[PDB]
Image (cartoon, coloured by chain):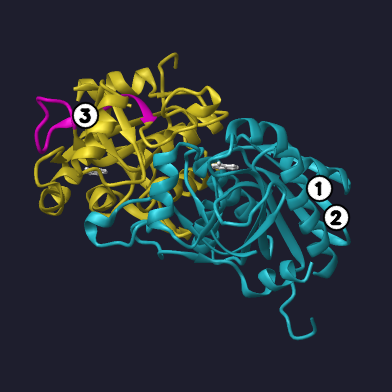
Chain colours: A yellow, B cyan
Amino acid sequence: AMDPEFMKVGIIGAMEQEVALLRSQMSNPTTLQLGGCEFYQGTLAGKEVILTRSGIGKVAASVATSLLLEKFAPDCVINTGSAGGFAQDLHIGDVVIASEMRFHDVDVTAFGYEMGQMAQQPAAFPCDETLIAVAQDCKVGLICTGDQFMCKPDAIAKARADFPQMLAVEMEGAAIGQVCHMFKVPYLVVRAMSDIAGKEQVESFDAFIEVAGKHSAEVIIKMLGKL
Amino acid sequence: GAMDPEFMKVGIIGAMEQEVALLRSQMSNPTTLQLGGCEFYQGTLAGKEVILTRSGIGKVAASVATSLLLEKFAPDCVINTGSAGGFAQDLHIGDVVIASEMRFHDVDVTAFGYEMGQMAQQPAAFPCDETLIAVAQDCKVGLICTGDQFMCKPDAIAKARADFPQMLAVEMEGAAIGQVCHMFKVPYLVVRAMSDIAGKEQVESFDAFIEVAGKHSAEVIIKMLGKL
Ligand SMILES: Nc1ncnc2[nH]cnc12
Ligand SMILES: Nc1ncnc2[nH]cnc12
């Protein structure tokens, strides 16, 4: 047709809680174990998908995404899961759609790069604008990524001062974005909040990870019907 | 030695041109593969079958490069070469450090009871292969830490020193390479040479001595290849 179509869809979640619902909706998925990650291929809500369980953190997400792209060559990558909320009117359970991802813990500013900009990379990784529109159809703005669980006052304050427009944080989104940039593949990050900055985040996370992961995944399921 | 395991196909990774140029020039008619924003050079080097890898800078690029290296070329080990910043007392520009183990200095999930530097679902440290370490020694030994920051401000250096009193040097890819090798279960080693020293005009130092650092590290690797 002449429609913006993504025929093979990659989906990636860090933890079992972020991928279990998706996997359970798949028609007789095939499972591959590779590089410490898991890949499940099959059909889901009508679409051809590769669902990936990456593990937590930038390194794990990067090997997951790079294996996904090299071995399966999807047409786009959608990352789903939970995040920590920073924007004022954000609550537990709220969804944020990323317009772009940045790293909040990257600092090579001694060499002229922007805060959060890794050498040889762009400062930010914009999400595909079609994927954003589809997600909206089913808050939009900046999410930042770092290899730390944000819950101490000073760390939260530094991150707010560095990125005043940051809406939420997590531990994989910008890595996935970077790898997709390195491979030139469209992507999107969708997160639901499992905790809010300054508000008992450890206990919150443990209590809300399951339902936040489901909530995010349900947006993705809705998306798959319109793609 | 006779009792040591063998490594028939050797993977070598450097972040920057300055860290792989010399090694590449000593390869015999290398094939080149461009993929995922990385480059792979396949051929013979100092008598060994090798895949030399130019990864790009930082944890994410190193991770991509190492994933692809391993899944596409399946080498029997991985050796990381390049520059680092010195922390230990008696390090000077150009000095070589062999990693006995890698840790991340910027990873912090301690709120969940993990050690400082330990990523969730990962060990706290990634020990380098017992055979490779000894081969490098035959050609300081200790902890090198990795983070996605160029380390040169006083507060940053002091904190890293506080979290890791045993850290000899810092750089930006080694423990990522180690984690990926751990995930694939493949032997690895990190060798680095100092391009700058903590607190001493590090931006200028790095700019001036990245090439000599890349060189000294690469020379060790060439010698290692001679003994594998
Ligand atoms: N507070 C937080 N920091 C980092 N990653 C998170 N994922 C969910 N909540 C998070
Ligand atoms: N000071 C430094 N910090 C991080 N990586 C480095 N590589 C070389 N020097 C470095």
What secondary structure is found at the residue carrying circle 2?
strand
**Which one is nearer the viewer's eye here, B120 or B212?**
B212
Disc 1 marks which residue?
B23
**Front tag of 3 and 2:** 2
Residue type beneath disc 2: Leu
**Front tag of 1 and 3:** 1
Residue type beneath disc 1: Leu
Q: Chain of mark 2?
A: B
Q: Are marks 3 and 2 on the same chain?
A: no
Q: State the residue at coordinates (77%, 68%).
A: B8
Q: Are marks 1 and 2 in contact (CB under 8 Å)?
A: yes
Q: Chain of mark 3?
A: A
In the figure, is residue A155 to the left or right of A89?
A: right
The span picked out in magenta is: A86-102
Distance in Å between CA atoms under marks 3 and 2: 50 Å
Disc 3 marks which residue?
A96
Q: Chain of mark 1?
A: B
Disc 2 marks which residue?
B45
Point out residue A119 in the picture as x, y percentages from the top left corner.
55, 30
Tally of numbered tags = 3
Point out residue B216 in the picture as x, y percentages from the top left corner.
77, 50
